[PDB]
Image (cartoon, rainbow, N blue to C red; front, side):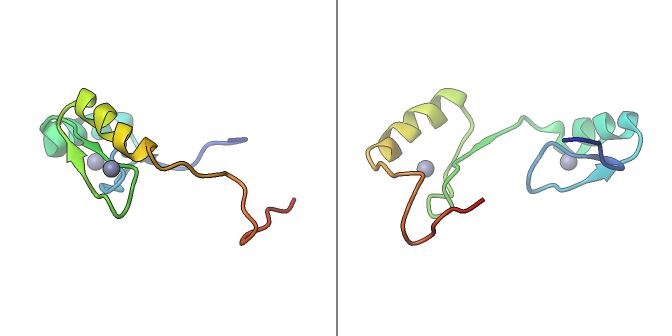
Length: 79
Ligand SMILES: [Zn+2]
Ligand SMILES: [Zn+2]
């Protein structure tokens, strides 16, 4: 994050909107995203969603069951 970028991107991931002036952004979120924010699962295959913060947390619990290592042979990290 050495330097910033032009325009101001939206918060929502799917949205993918950009607005030069901030005023517009806030208005866009208050208008388009007027609705209440939501929580999505960080898993692609899961594609689950929860309208409650607690729900997401508890949901993850299950996933936890499966553990993994940041490092792997298949893809040797270099640099
Ligand atoms: Zn947006
Ligand atoms: Zn999930």
